[PDB]
Image: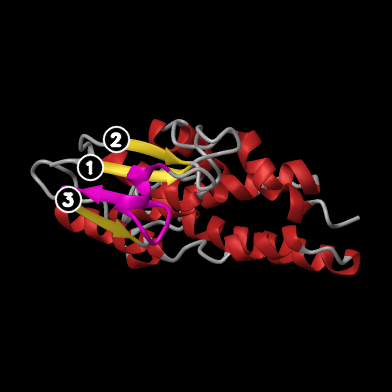
Amino acid sequence: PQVELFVKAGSDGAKIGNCPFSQRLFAVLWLKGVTFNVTTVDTKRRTETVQKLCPGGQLPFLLYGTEVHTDTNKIEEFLEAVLCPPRYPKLAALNPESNTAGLDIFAKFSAYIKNSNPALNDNLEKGLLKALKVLDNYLTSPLPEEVDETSAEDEGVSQRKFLDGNELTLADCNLLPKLHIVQVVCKKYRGFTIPEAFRGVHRYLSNAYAREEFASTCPDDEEIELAYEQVAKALK
């Protein structure tokens, strides 16, 4: 069954570019354990093949068998439904709220990073921090699998590695590529780092960077910084 992911190329026309949608599906496919290929597209210099496969030009897209699929959310839903046990793990979260935890962070970041009004900087940095804190509280809330298991010193605190438990799920595949952009960009252009006191978020990121599915699908930091340079530099 042939599976080829087409993804956004970076500044050299070849390496992985900044696209958290590309990276989400790359990670889903890696987690499924299916055999697949990844082909980068320089959208300024498209191949005759890519032009034929996807006239509409959407990116990312997926060639599966002879069918071309577009729309990241739909492509992911398709993959989860078609790549099924026993050959491939189900990657859907068990707890619905894992699928919404921290979904606001990226738009708070986008406002913060596009803002060029100095009087609103602190408001927008607050908005971002508040959204990150709500993610932190999700990551430290025990989930049903952890029911009544603890230690005297950390009662009512979750020990789990990722959003929905100790395995990576589709929820992590959506969130992590975006959280990665937020970190990289805000360090470079805002002097901002996530507070050390968000221990849940910190642990989450520590565990996520330790996983090739996330770590090996990340664009180079440089690609992410270049992608944001024009809109991030406007604030003086």
Label 2 vs label 1: CA separation?
6 Å
Label 2 vs label 3: CA separation?
14 Å
Q: Closer to the camera, 78 or 176?
A: 78
The residue drawn where x is 83% and y is 56% is: 234
The spot of residue 167 in percent (x, y) is 32, 43
Lower sequence index among marks 2 and 1: 1
The residue drawn where x is 39% and y is 63% is: 99
Q: Amino acid at mark 2?
A: Asn
Label 2 crowding class (10 Å Cα cut-off): few <14, some 14-19, many 20+?
few
Magenta highlight on residue 96: no
Q: Secondary structure at mark 1?
A: strand
Label 3 crowding class (10 Å Cα cut-off): few <14, some 14-19, many 20+?
few
Residue pointed to by mark 1: 3
Left or right: 190, with 209 as reference point? right
Left or right: 125, with 79 as reference point? right
Q: Closer to the camera, 194 or 199?
A: 194
Res. 211 in view: yes
The spot of residue 48 in percent (x, y) is 36, 44
Q: Nearer the viewer, mark 2 or mark 3?
A: 3
Disc 2 and disc 1 in contact, CB within 8 angstroms: yes
Residue pointed to by mark 2: 37
The residue drawn where x is 59% and y is 60% is: 106
Q: Secondary structure at mark 3?
A: loop
Q: Closer to the camera, 191 or 207?
A: 191
Q: Which residue of the protein is positioned furthest toward the front in this rendering?
A: 48
Q: Amino acid at mark 3?
A: Thr
Q: Amino acid at mark 1?
A: Val
Range drawn in magenta: 47-66
Residue pointed to by mark 3: 66
Quick one: quadrant of the N terminus? top left
Q: Secondary structure at mark 2?
A: strand
